[PDB]
Amino acid sequence: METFAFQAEIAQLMSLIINTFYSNKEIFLRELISNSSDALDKIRYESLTDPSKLDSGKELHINLIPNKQDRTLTIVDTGIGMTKADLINNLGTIAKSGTKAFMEALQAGADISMIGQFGVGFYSAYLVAEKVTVITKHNDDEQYAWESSAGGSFTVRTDTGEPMGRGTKVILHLKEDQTEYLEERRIKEIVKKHSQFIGYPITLFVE
Ligand SMILES: Cc1onc(-c2ccc(O)cc2O)c1-c1ccccc1
Image (cartoon, rainbow, N blue to C red; front, side, top):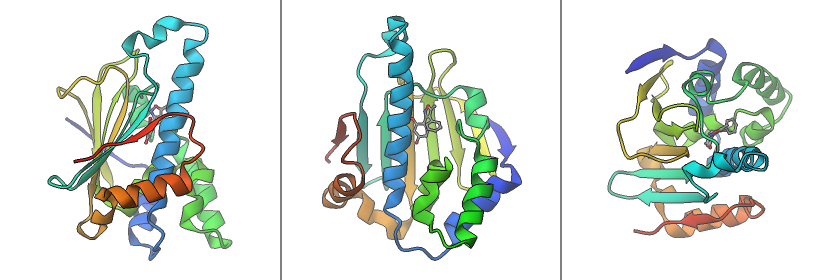
């Protein structure tokens, strides 16, 4: 396992998300499903000129898996996936510049729900999760596990777990007061409200 320090700007973003009083936490799901949709578009685009890109899996979907016993909400997609370099470089984002633009917008009157307009929507996971684990597999690299409970650092390791073919799995270890996001009715409500125009099947698993 390798441990890395977040860039100062990203540690500042995470602290703002964790510490700011902001009741509209539900937007984390829209942000994560939006990232999944973007990753699925990328592999579909590459497959148009190279059909062998889909040898690691032809299905393009998003699965939402709540687990009440482990207190986790997992979002699985079969998108392009991230390489080790992508994971280290802020999960494939330009997060340093995105954070700068987002923080300026917040000072001017914008609110936390607009985070996605700054290309740093992933970090909204910290509105509801005490720890986030990202398992990812890109065609050109091995399967990795990224993890962070914030606190200024993240870890990366080769994942020896269940092989995923291709794509990304985001495991949200929920905060104790955020268990409403494991309830079927609550998840359905959020998906219908914010993700009605996502062009891939979104399957809400049951227990
Ligand atoms: C590329 C890529 O490959 N997997 C993800 C991914 C990142 C986060 C996530 O929640 C789900 C995902 O599929 C992304 C990605 C990187 C930056 C912006 C949007 C997608």
